Image 1 (cartoon, rainbow, N blue to C red):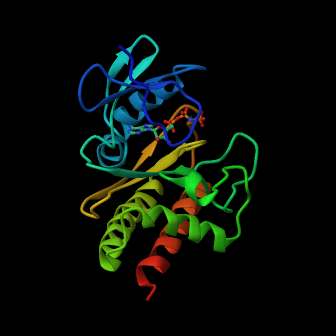
Image 2 (image 1 turned 60 degrees about the vertical axis):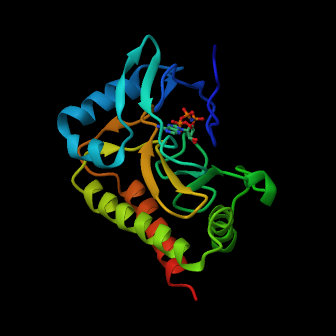
Length: 216
Ligand SMILES: Nc1ncnc2c1ncn2[C@@H]1O[C@H](COP(=O)(O)OP(=O)(O)NP(=O)(O)O)[C@@H](O)[C@H]1O
């Protein structure tokens, strides 16, 4: 009938598609997420190809989207808001961890403002549930760093304010493959410059992840 999707964060009605590899996200407030997908498609298709989950189509108010967790045996997922919050400063300065797999088990609260110490430990907690193998964690961090690097670089040439967008970090329990993608275009806007706020979010995450990958 209807299988509801294991969101890691956010408020939206998201369900498994009737078919493999798809989730349906309801647009609650407006069709702005759909208008923005189609804008990015026409003006920046390379950005869409590399970083954004595929939009397969629309069914009334629902978006048929690529399930990012589909190709994984045991996904571990972390949602980090890197674009500006509606009102409210970021819980970790330049970004906000909205949640992660097993966050309850480390008494993570999305409203708690965090020192640089807490922030790092919460990312380390995210890495624990697979991790263990010291240098499968390095390979996961380094592959995330590789992609966020290209993303931070590519953002300089993109005239959008990425208000409210998130990074979805995934890795498998048996620390093989991993990925990070940009999601949630519902409050994204056109502007005549780049988004220095969102760039600082990504560069800061790159800094934090590099520190963990170098850590002995
Ligand atoms: N393409 C995707 N593949 C897999 N999981 C996804 C995908 N898109 C969204 N999610 C999951 O859904 C959660 C929230 O959906 P998101 O697209 O961020 O918007 P939202 O629900 O409108 N949030 P908000 O209005 O700020 O409360 C994420 O934290 C992920 O766990």
